[PDB]
Each structure stands twice: as structure tokens, then as C-alpha cells.
Length: 275
Ligand SMILES: Nc1ncnc2c1ncn2[C@@H]1O[C@H](COP(=O)(O)OP(=O)(O)OP(=O)(O)O)[C@@H](O)[C@H]1O
Ligand SMILES: O=P(O)(O)OC[C@@H]1O[C@H](CO)[C@@H](OP(=O)(O)O)[C@H](OP(=O)(O)O)[C@H]1O
Ligand SMILES: [Mn+2]
Image (tube, rainbow, N blue to C red):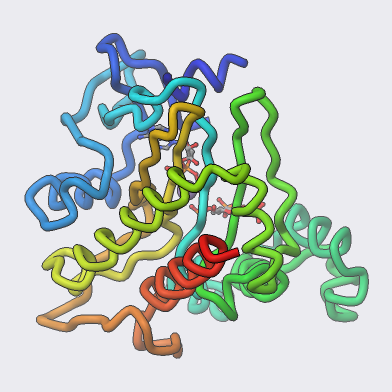
């Protein structure tokens, strides 16, 4: 029905207009959503209606993706082999900010993961933490990871930090769709059409897409949709330079593995459909 309904039961606020939601404005994301409304990917992203002022702060006015659903189930999938900008590697070499928060979450999952010096510091750099997170999840090997589920029973979970194997990922989607063959068929048709759109998009060949998600939404009436969201770390390549979005990332090449991820995700859902 609406996201703010679920919120009530960080960057999001309720809109006055029915079927809309407000997200805190960031300049990279505003730039991206403006370009996307004129791109092949227009129908694969939430409608962007412009910027509004609320309590002396700027908000993006977005389509509420939950509006058309009756008690929506939601799964957020972070896309890419890399989840941080290359500039973070330069900042950590020249002038590191030590993160005590990030050391604690590391310790919790694997006490043996931090180095002798990190244990002494009780702190790690951002790129070190994010690379570790990529390696214990499916990010490094499959090019995507499950971040969270919000269920129609009001229950939610973010307990997926060690979901890594192809079969572990398949079991999360198996539980999410609860044997609804129509929802799974509609998700697979939508992902195939999104892949075709990405492969011809003028926006996609010219931009590094880091930290974006695919948002899966379905309901008990068998309605099913998928959209790209979160363009806060999506940046244009210099000159007339393009990415293939499949080849491995090496510092300098700005590759994101986005389509390696989408290829693997379609393969897993196609496998699940034949079980
Ligand atoms: N247009 C939308 N309509 C409905 N729900 C949305 C919409 N955009 C985002 N959401 C919800 O908000 C969540 C967070 O979205 P998003 O990733 O854009 O935010 P964020 O604050 O940048 O988070 P992060 O950067 O940590 O991933 C999504 O997983 C989804 O549940
Ligand atoms: O491992 P998780 O699930 O707990 O997520 C950790 C958080 O992942 C965010 C991305 O989703 C980062 O944000 P940006 O990438 O927009 O910069 C946060 O970074 P900062 O703390 O530096 O803002 C980081 O703490
Ligand atoms: Mn996000």
C-alpha cells in the first residue's frame, strides 16, 4: 500500500500527494533520476517528479513503489561485486578515518578476521570493512547480495550477512515467494526485460553504478514488480569512456560487475522455477 505505513508499523518522509514518498535529496541521486526519466530505463526506476522543500530541507518526490499492492512483501538486493567508490581507496591510503563501529561488526561475525594492528586500534578503514562484507556474503562471487526482507505479516529481517552460496541465496527466494508460481514467473519476465533495457541504455553504458538495489515487491493477489533504486553513488565516466558491467573490477577500471550479478540472479530464479 505505502512504505511510510510500514515505517510507522531514516532518509524517507510521507508526501502530501497520494501514491508518492519523499527521500532526502543528494546531488548525485538527483542528477541520475533526472537523466533516467529520459532514458530507456524510465520504466525500470521509480517516477521522479522533482524536488520539494519541507522544514527547510530538500526532498526528491518519488513514486511509492508499494502503492499498487495489497499487503506487499519486499526484498532488497544490493547489485555489484564492489559496494564503495574507488576514491575511498585513495582516502584510506593518504588520510584514513579509523571506524570503531565497523571493527565491532567484523569481530562479531569472525573474531579471527581483524589483523593484530586492527585489534590494537579497535578500528578498521571503510574500504577494508566493505571488502570483508563483500567476501562473507555473495557479493564478491555472484555480484549481488540479499540485504533485507519485509513480510506481509509486518515482520522484517536483515539477518543475511553470511548468505553466500548459490543454494543459500536460492533458499531465501524460495521462502520469500512461498510457492506462488505466478509471482516467480512475473519476477523472471520482469528481470529478463530489465536486462534487455540495461544492455541498450545510453545512461547505463556511460555510468558506474555502485550501491544500487533491485527492489522485489509482490502480494497475495499475485501482483509482482521489480525496480532499480538508490543512485546516491552512481557517477558518469570521463571523456567518452564506457563500462561492459561484466568484467572483473581492478582499481582504475571503475567496473561494477552489475550485469554479472543480474545474470547470476536470473539463473538462480530460473533454477528455483524448475524445482
Ligand atoms: N520509491 C520507493 N518506494 C517505496 N519504497 C522505497 C522506495 N525507495 C526506497 N524504498 C524503500 O526504502 C529502502 C531504502 O531505500 P534506498 O536504498 O534508496 O535508501 P538509502 O537510505 O540510500 O539506503 P542505503 O544507502 O543504506 O542502501 C528500500 O529497501 C525500500 O524498502
Ligand atoms: O554492512 P552494513 O549493512 O551495516 O552497512 C554499512 C553501511 O553501508 C552503507 C551502504 O549501504 C554505507 O553508506 P554509503 O555507501 O552511502 O557511504 C555506510 O557508510 P558510512 O558509515 O561511511 O556512511 C556503511 O556504514
Ligand atoms: Mn540503498
